Image 1 (cartoon, rainbow, N blue to C red):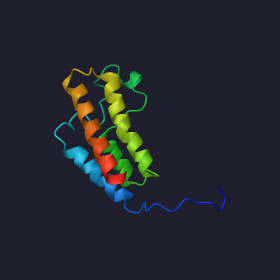
Image 2: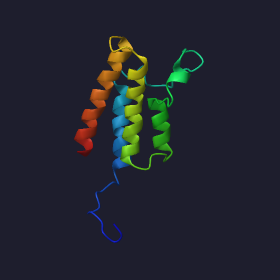
Image 3: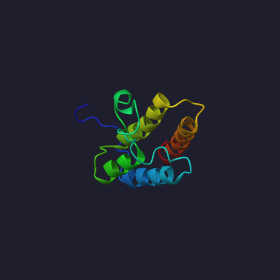
Length: 115
């Protein structure tokens, strides 16, 4: 509350560390569905169904331009990529499998870097 604060967690390295995580997600062999925005002209249904499209290149640009206020808003966009994927793709598809794999990979790196 006013003039009553928990001890200050050091957040000075968060930007660099989210960047490192994102590099690792970018270079994963199963990243290919997620590297670029879904082409809304070429994929029927996407535009109407997926209300907030998100992809790795868009997160990279937001990260690089100070559009994440804190590490939680960064994680929300990463998870949005996977939540979008599960909304549009069958589990038993190459893309559906990719999304599950990448979500796992991310959640581990997230816990190990920060929790």
